[PDB]
């Protein structure tokens, strides 16, 4: 089943917090360690999420964070996930800055690409792919998390392309203009995630307002090459940022290209 009773969970340590609610490390009965995300009232369209949870849980891949179930008996609801020991990739990059080999950084991009090629084949669009939405686990494996979750967020300032909080830094032009999501808009976001990885967690378009990012991208500006990215890796990042979605590589193509670079 996909419904987890409240008696099947324990809450050991709070590990995260934000406007969504809280995250705890806990245990799940007869099924080991978990991260439990408690959702604040009004943050999410809970009925829409609960309607799709069972189908969402069948998206299972070694490079995707597994959703194990939903505790919905009483408010607030909890979502129960696979526990990732090193936390979000954005913070992991920042705290370990200066300690990465370029091969490790490319390997993190490959893990994300592998999870995204699975979602692309399943015709599942992430919509908000970024280093903050990737988690680091056993042996520094990266896994993609929160795919499709912006479909349930109730904060219009974050979900509307004209919203004050919209994540325009990772959005392709057709997303920041029209909310035209596709696997090719996720590819643009993946180019920005690659830039976050090779820069060791710098924030893209630092200090630029949302309208300034739109004006810059529309006028051909692109993120500068990080020092640790080779010319060839930066070439692939620029292919992710092609203005037309049709000219961007699919994740299946990126996965072969990046693997050839890593394995050579
Ligand atoms: C800060 C933090 C947040 C973490 N968030 C998650 C996490 N795992 N899975 C999900 C999520 C987050 C989100 C619920 C998901 C969709 C899925 N892992 C996390 C690990 C840490 N790190 C680096 C720690 O040092 C914490 C304090 N430690 C780790 C060792 O064990 C003891 C506690």
Image (cartoon, rainbow, N blue to C red):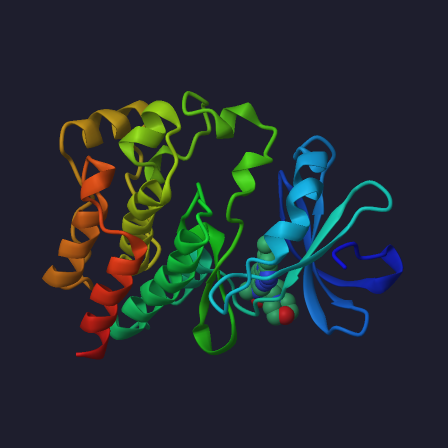
Residue furthest to the left: 231
- Classify 44 as above or below 188: above
Viewed as shown, does residue 180 lie left or right of 57? left
Image spot of residue 24 (x, y percent): 70, 58
- Classify 202 as above or below 11: above
- Classify 16 as above or below 43: below
- Classify 12 as above or below 119: below
Viewed as shown, does residue 193 lie left or right of 237? right
Q: Is residue 127 visible?
A: yes
In this view, the residue in front, 169 or 255, is 255
Image spot of residue 117 (x, y percent): 37, 58
User: Which quadrant of the figure shows ligand 1?
Assistant: bottom right
Dividing the picture into quadrants, the one containing residue 211 is: top left
Q: Quadrant of the C terminus?
A: bottom left
What residue sits 22% from the left and 46% below the top? 248
Residue furthest to the top: 162
In this view, the residue in front, 184 or 168, is 184
- The mark tally for this picture is 0
Viewed as shown, does residue 131 lie left or right of 188? right
Q: Is residue 98 visible?
A: no
Image spot of residue 102 (x, y percent): 24, 71
What residue sits 14% from the left and 64% below the top? 230
What residue sits 57% from the left and 67% below the top? 84
Q: Quadrant of the N terminus?
A: bottom right
Viewed as shown, does residue 125 lie left or right of 214? right
């Amino acid at each position: 089943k996909w419904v987890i009773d409240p008696s099947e969970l324990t809450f050991v340590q709070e590990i995260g917090s934000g406007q969504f609610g809280l995250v705890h490390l806990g245990y799940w009965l007869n099924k080991d360690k978990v991260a439990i995300k408690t959702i604040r009232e009004g943050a999410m369209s809970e009925e829409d999420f609960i309607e799709e949870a069972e189908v969402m849980m069948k998206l299972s891949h070694p490079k995707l964070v597994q959703l194990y179930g939903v505790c919905l008996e009483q408010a607030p609801i909890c979502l129960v996930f696979e526990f990732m020991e090193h936390g979000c990739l954005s913070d992991y990059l920042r705290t370990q800055r200066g300690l990465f080999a370029a091969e490790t950084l490319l390997g993190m991009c490959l893990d994300v690409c592998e999870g995204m090629a699975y979602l692309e084949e399943a015709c599942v669009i992430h919509r908000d792919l970024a280093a903050r939405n990737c988690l680091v686990g056993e042996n520094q494996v990266i896994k993609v998390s929160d795919f499709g979750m912006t479909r349930f967020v109730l904060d219009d300032q974050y979900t509307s392309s004209t919203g004050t909080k919209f994540p325009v830094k990772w959005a392709s032009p057709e997303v920041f203009s029209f909310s035209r999501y596709s696997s090719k808009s996720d590819v643009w976001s993946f180019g920005v995630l690659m830039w976050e990885v090779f820069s060791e967690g710098k924030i893209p378009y630092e200090n630029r307002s949302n309208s300034e990012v739109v004006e810059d991208i529309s006028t051909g500006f692109r993120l500068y090459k990080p020092r640790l990215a080779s010319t060839h890796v930066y070439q692939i990042m620029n292919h992710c940022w092609r203005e037309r979605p049709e000219d961007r590589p699919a994740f299946s193509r990126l996965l072969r290209q990046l693997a050839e670079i890593a394995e050579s």
